[PDB]
Image (cartoon, rainbow, N blue to C red; front, side, top):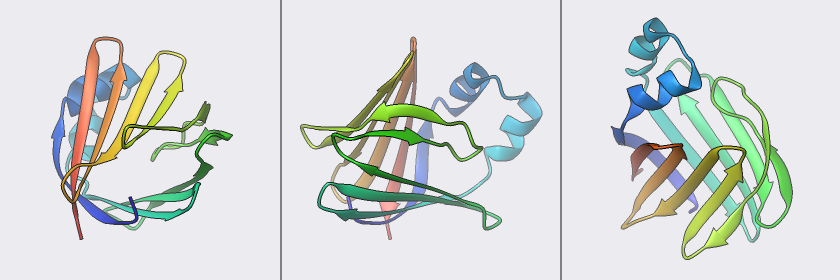
Length: 125
């Protein structure tokens, strides 16, 4: 997982963002942000950073198997426990499922809420 990754692809961004309840005007603007993810893994400990066009940053620090609270790029916090399952980091929370995986030097992140699945693929820098 350790690396710096730049988003190159995403599936179902609009459908996912509407479900979060964010305005169409903000969806349209936010769609054009470049997202760079920087990850540092030290054993069980992760530091996980998202850097957005403009220089805003969101950092989460968690231990696999420990309860933690995660915040999102905008700033919405939630309690969760990250599990290592088959190569994936997996997170759960009321009505929300999230995975992060390295697939052939790419970082692939999947979030599912109900029938809606968002995917992000980020190339390694």
